[PDB]
């Protein structure tokens, strides 16, 4: 017949299929355009999502009814100890797309990455890379030939980095390895940079800075098998209805005589890949800085960790990125921060922030105190104690 | 003289500005056309302090005061207070007042000699006002309205009250305030003369919509 | 919102869907306001239009002077009760739902407003500012 | 920002949070954990309520 | 201060109107899916077509009736201005035509829907729609000549000078080329405007001047009031009469010099004829352009104006030259004062 009343579809066809992602490490499907005039640097970074908290800052938006007033804002924090560089991989342009032609590895590989190449570490003879490592013995010659080849050919150079998971409260020991496109100028300069950085270490301040707009690429929280109502935001059917009501009443017309790809159905929910963009960096933390969670306006020596510590995560004892708002994925997940694909002029992006205050109270209840110092002050002396 | 302007497209100047004989307060996020209205005729004469009160920009309704003092709501932040103390001359006292009848600017109407207050104000508060503003205070109603600061524009030269104020109240109020009072309207018919314009002994700023007759009464009664 | 509303308004939690009755908080003779429409509200199958603080509604007077009853007029919501959240981080709420009868331009029919008035409404409708005592 | 203290608990409210309702007096009271609000609505006696700052004062819980 | 008359929208022609209705009905019929009996479905389609046929006619005709204040209802100044252009008597029959047409289309639509609704025969149902379309088609075509007259007038009424007949106006009259247009521009503070009007040679110059927070409107008459009223056509004679409603005060400019190309004797005659008629409105006669003016003419002027003897408006003339800008503000205050200060006290 014809609908009756018009309404928009439930849910976005551009995020199909709604199946579980092929890996907890969401893929970077694109990198920034290359500007080979600038210095060589990474274009993304690995970290772990730890938690959120609240911020207060004064706003700067000439014209807003909130210009020059304080706002309070949710932000998230991602643990970010220096990534360590261990390979370069060199790609070439073909009429069938980008194809990698070599990979050169550092001579010494940390147990952390080595562990990544294995399914049962405890039993294994840990032989990974033990013949590659030899290639260095000899003067250096075949590793030069490779490095050399990459320079000769190669349209784009990526770096194999991995995270220092041990520098993180996680149990998980096996580190995360991944390719990061290099955008500083000249294919040769790029590989030189790469080669120079083997076994050597790279920190976030070398990649991100205050007020930058960055993207988060990560696998979404999982939910298992979801009915149609919650998964697609379909209307609940009425109370009166027999044989269940969190459903879709009509699964299709009679012709085409086939349930169609575009109707909502029960199925997996969450644990999807997502490339969320335009998240402002409101803080770039330093792990060797007491007074991490302190401010120009605050002053009190205290770190970003909440009282009792980040619920379900742990402590934060390294550099971190504090991103305004909230990000795909959950507490503990490997998450990739990426440079933005365009120069946003937004004004909203561009505004330069300065935190006045960072919340620091326990998130494990309705916290009343920032430091244990403050808590003793307000509360008095207790039956434990002095 | 007397000028016309608008805060955005609003004629209620009294809502976004506070003018006395020794200082001028204006909302922080105004336009040049708005600010100029004052800068152009106050020049380097008296301080023109940009500010917010309790985080809002309706500073004209949120405060009350004269040459000697300024009254601000409790919710005035310490930052706004510090900024005010620093910008305004030392001879003016800035005091926080705790009253919940309405916004200070609606509850209080004053010049450098007398002040009318909401008729339901408590004694303690009425003494504080008299004290800080160094003025004689009287609980009154203008044509029945309790929001005196909203229905009365006053300077030391003259005053304008609700258009329906009887002649008898006008005569009595004139005597009480020691200045000629006349019932009138501002911004083309508005009877909220207190919020529609700001004024002191040498300048009156009203909204662009004030008619010719209304502006005539203004420069005539305030002697501009 | 709309006519005579000088200012924009930041979104605030919708408290009052159509059919809701708020206290009349002016001295017009009206005792309550029954919401039949929100101005500037959009469209989605099955959704009630619903007002908030400083929204202009279209109401009838269920209780009040007979010269006010049996007809539809504009009103403005002045107090909420559904809690909402400001950009200073605060979740706040009044003890009652209440608004005041008004004209399309936004002029109060009455001359007083009894009770407090949320600032977001005061900031929105100047003739409401005028007649307000305690704001927020 | 400065801290408004949730009066009932008397705890300092790190600038945001909670709700106001009007006493229909000049001031309004701020409320913390809803527990704080409900007890208040319960109209329980702060002198009795352990959580209250009042409890501390009266109780001996103090000086 | 504006025109009541502008608001009526332009009337579309019969030709535009014939096509649009059918096309719309055609669109409607295939989109619709009738439910029910086979015969009923077709019947439903035809009924739908008939009803869009009714709908389209009713919408156009309502637009003529709405938008428009009725010619009688408006204030006497405004009634007049319309009257010249169309002719009111022609206009009264024409208004009725629109109304009649609307009634008939509704009546026929009702007739056919019922007949089709009633009928079982498919051939009949089809024929009935055919008939209705035929009938609708003839009616718009017959009315085309009144539609054409209405459409043309809509544009002419829109052009009318927008001025207020209630509030005080000052009227500059005199023979043509006396310097009335210049006098007016000198008098007005802001730059002069031009208003189109029917049956005026130049158009009118309109200006305004303030003393206090009172506004005074000024218009000049060129070509309309300037010459014998009787000599003019029935439409133009009526245009002259519209000025009567409009003016609160009349000023008579004389140019003695004969630079205007007209003698003082002629100017005195025209003035005298108009003068007793408007007792109700104040008069200020000003002999302007004084610097150039010749003494030979002055004697004739003096005999009407200054002399208590026959024909005299009882007003005291101001010598000036506004063009020269000597006494321009002095003359202007007096002209406003003569009607204003009066009217205030009067009322």
Image: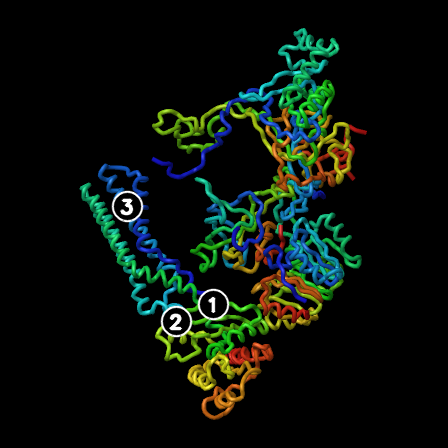
Residue A371: x %, y % from top left: 75, 33
Mark-to-mark CA distance, 3 and 2? 44 Å
Q: Are marks 2 and 1 in contact (CB under 8 Å)?
A: no
- Chain of the residue under label 3: E
Marks 3, 1: nearer the viewer = 1
- Chain of the residue under label 1: E
Q: Which residue does the image show at 63% across and 16% down from the upper left?
A: A102
- Callout 1: few (<14), some (14-19), or many (20+) C-alpha neighbours within 10 Å? some
Q: How many marks?
A: 3
Disc 2, SS: helix
- Which one is nearer the viewer's eye here, A196 or E121? A196
Residue B195: x %, y % from top left: 63, 60
Of callouts 3 and 1, which one flags the residue occurring earlier in the amino acid sequence? 3
Quadrant into which the C terminus of chain A falls: top right
Q: Provide the residue designation for mark 3.
A: E49
Q: Which residue does the image show at 47% across and 46% down from the upper left?
A: C18
User: Taking B168 as reference, is A368 above or below it?
Assistant: above
Mark-to-mark CA distance, 3 and 1? 48 Å
Marks 2, 1: nearer the viewer = 1
Q: Which residue does the image show at 39% across and 25% down from the upper left?
A: A259
């Amino acid at each position: 017949s014809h609908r009756k009343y018009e309404a928009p579809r439930h849910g976005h066809l551009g995020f199909l299929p709604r199946k579980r992602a092929a890996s907890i490490r969401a893929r970077v499907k694109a990198f920034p355009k290359d500007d080979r005039s600038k210095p060589v640097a990474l274009t993304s970074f690995l970290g772990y999502k730890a938690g959120m908290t609240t911020i207060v800052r004064d706003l700067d938006r000439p014209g807003s009814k909130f210009h020059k007033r304080e706002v309070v804002e949710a932000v998230t924090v991602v643990d970010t100890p220096p990534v360590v560089v261990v390979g370069v991989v060199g790609y070439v342009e073909t009429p069938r797309g980008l194809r990698s032609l070599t990979t050169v590895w550092a001579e010494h590989l940390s147990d952390e990455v080595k562990r990544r190449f294995y399914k049962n570490w405890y039993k294994s003879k840990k032989k990974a890379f033990t013949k590659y490592s030899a290639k260095y013995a000899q003067d250096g010659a075949g590793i030069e030939r490779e490095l050399a080849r990459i320079k000769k050919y190669a349209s784009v150079v990526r770096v194999l980095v991995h995270t220092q998971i041990r520098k993180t409260p996680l149990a998980q020991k096996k580190a995360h390895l991944a390719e990061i496109q290099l955008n500083g100028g000249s294919i040769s300069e790029k590989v030189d940079w790469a080669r120079e950085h083997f076994e050597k270490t790279v920190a976030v301040d070398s990649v991100f800075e205050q007020n930058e707009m960055i993207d988060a690429i990560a696998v979404t929280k999982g939910h298992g098998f979801e009915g149609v109502t919650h998964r697609w935001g379909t209307k609940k059917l009425p109370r009166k209805t027999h044989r269940g009501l969190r459903k879709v009443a009509c699964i299709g017309a009679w012709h085409p005589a086939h349930v169609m790809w575009s109707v909502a159905r029960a199925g997996q929910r969450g644990y999807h890949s997502r490339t969320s963009i335009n998240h402002k960096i409101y803080r770039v933390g330093k792990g060797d800085d007491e007074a991490n969670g302190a401010t120009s306006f605050d002053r009190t020596k205290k770190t970003i960790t909440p009282m009792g510590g980040f619920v379900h995560y742990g402590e934060i004892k390294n550099d971190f990125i504090m991103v305004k708002g909230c990000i795909p994925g959950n507490r503990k997940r490997i998450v990739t921060l990426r440079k933005s694909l365009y120069t946003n002029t937004s004004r909203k992006a561009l505004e330069e922030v300065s935190l006045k205050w960072i919340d620091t109270a326990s998130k494990f209840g309705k916290g009343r105190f920032q430091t244990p110092a403050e808590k003793h002050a307000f509360m008095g002396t207790l039956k434990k104690d002095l | 003289m007397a000028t016309r302007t608008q805060f955005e497209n609003s004629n209620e100047i009294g809502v976004f500005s506070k003018l006395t004989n020794t200082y001028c307060l204006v909302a922080v996020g105004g336009s040049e056309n708005f600010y100029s209205a004052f800068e152009a005729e106050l020049g380097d004469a008296i301080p023109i302090v940009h500010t917010t009160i309790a985080g809002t920009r309706i500073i004209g309704r949120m405060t009350a005061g004269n040459r000697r003092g300024l009254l601000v709501p409790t919710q005035t932040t310490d930052q706004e207070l510090q900024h005010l103390r620093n910008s305004l001359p030392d001879s003016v006292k800035i005091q926080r007042v705790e009253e919940r009848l309405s916004a200070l600017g609606n509850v209080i109407c004053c010049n450098d000699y007398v002040a009318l207050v909401h008729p339901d104000i408590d004694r303690e508060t009425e003494e504080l006002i008299s004290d800080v503003l160094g003025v004689e205070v009287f609980r009154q109603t203008i044509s029945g309205n309790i929001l005196v600061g909203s229905y009365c524009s006053l300077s030391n030269q003259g005053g304008l009250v609700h258009p329906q104020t009887s002649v008898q109240d006008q005569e009595e109020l004139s005597s009480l305030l020691q200045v000629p009072l006349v019932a009138g309207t501002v911004n083309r018919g508005s009877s909220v003369v207190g919020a529609g314009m700001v004024v002191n002994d040498y300048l009156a700023v009203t909204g662009l919509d004030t008619t010719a007759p209304e502006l005539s009464v203004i420069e005539s009664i305030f002697r501009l | 919102s709309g006519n005579g509303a000088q200012g924009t308004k930041f979104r605030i939690s919708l408290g009052l869907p159509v059919g809701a009755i708020m206290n009349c908080a002016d001295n017009s003779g009206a005792r309550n306001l029954y919401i039949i429409a929100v101005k500037g509200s959009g469209s989605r199958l099955n959704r009630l239009p619903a007002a908030s603080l400083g929204d202009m509604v279209m109401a009838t007077v269920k209780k009040g002077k007979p010269e006010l009853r049996k007809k539809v007029m504009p009103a403005i919501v002045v107090r909420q009760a559904k809690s909402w959240r400001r950009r200073d981080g605060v979740f706040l709420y009044f003890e009652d739902n209440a608004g005041v009868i008004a004209n399309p331009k936004g002029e109060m029919k009455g001359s007083a407003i009894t009770g407090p008035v949320g600032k977001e409404c005061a900031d929105l409708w100047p003739r409401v500012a005028s007649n307000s005592g305690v704001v927020v | 920002m400065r801290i408004y203290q949730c009066h009932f608990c008397s705890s300092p409210c790190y600038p945001g949070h909670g709700i106001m309702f009007v006493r229909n007096d000049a001031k309004e009271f701020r409320f913390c954990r809803s527990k704080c609000h409900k007890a208040f609505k319960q109209r329980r006696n702060p002198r009795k309520l352990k959580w209250t700052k009042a409890f501390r004062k009266a109780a001996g819980k103090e000086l | 201060m504006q025109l009541s008359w502008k608001d009526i929208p332009t009337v579309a022609p019969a030709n535009d109107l014939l096509d649009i209705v059918l096309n719309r009905t055609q669109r409607k019929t295939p989109t619709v899916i009738r439910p029910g009996f086979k015969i009923t479905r077709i019947r439903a389609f035809y009924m739908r077509k008939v009803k869009y046929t009714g709908e389209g006619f009713v919408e156009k005709f309502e637009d003529i009736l709405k938008g428009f204040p009725n010619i009688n209802d408006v204030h006497p100044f405004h009634r007049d201005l319309m009257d010249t252009l169309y002719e009111k008597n022609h206009y009264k029959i024409s208004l009725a035509a629109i109304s009649r047409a609307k009634s008939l289309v509704e009546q026929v639509a009702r007739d056919y829907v019922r007949l089709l609704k009633f009928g079982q025969s498919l051939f009949q149902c089809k024929q009935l729609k055919r008939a209705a379309l035929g009938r609708m088609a003839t009616i718009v075509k017959k009315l085309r000549d009144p539609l054409a007259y209405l459409e043309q007038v809509r544009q002419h009424i829109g052009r009318l000078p927008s001025i207020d007949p209630n509030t005080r106006t000052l009227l500059i009259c005199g023979y043509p080329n006396v310097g009335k247009s210049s006098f007016l521009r000198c008098i007005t503070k802001s730059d002069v405007d031009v208003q189109p009007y029917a049956f005026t040679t130049k158009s009118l110059y309109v200006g305004h001047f303030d003393y206090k927070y009172l506004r005074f409107q000024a218009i000049d008459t060129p070509g309309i009031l300037d010459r014998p009223t009787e000599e003019m056509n029935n439409i133009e004679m009526q245009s002259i009469y519209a000025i009567a409603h409009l003016r609160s005060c009349v000023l008579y400019f004389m140019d003695l010099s004969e630079q205007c190309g007209f003698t003082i004797e002629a100017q005195v005659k025209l003035f005298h004829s108009i003068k007793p008629l408007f007792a109700n409105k104040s008069v200020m006669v000003v002999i302007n352009k004084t610097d150039i003016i010749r003494p030979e003419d002055l004697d004739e002027e003096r005999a009407q104006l200054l002399e208590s003897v026959k024909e005299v408006p009882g007003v005291e003339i101001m010598t000036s030259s506004c063009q020269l800008e000597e006494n321009v503000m002095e003359v202007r205050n007096k002209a406003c004062e003569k009607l204003l200060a009066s009217r205030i006290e009067n009322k």
